[PDB]
Amino acid sequence: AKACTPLLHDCSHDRHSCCRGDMFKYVCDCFYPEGEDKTEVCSCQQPKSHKIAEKIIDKAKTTL
Image (cartoon, rainbow, N blue to C red):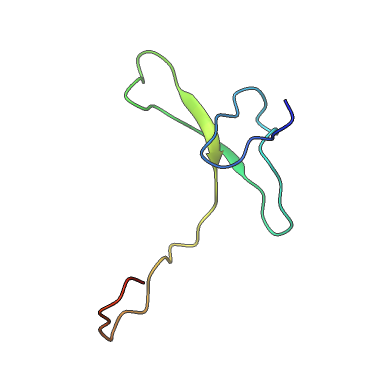
């Protein structure tokens, strides 16, 4: 496998196979995509800071 395991990609092959960066790396996360009774899916997910939009006091008629 030449290409690595970026975000939104399964990393069951290796919890530490997910691609890497200069600032922050990708963390493997497992979830039950409607298959908690069948099997769990583990993909690469990125961190957060509980802040995706905290500046919209003013209006704007244009795609942000």
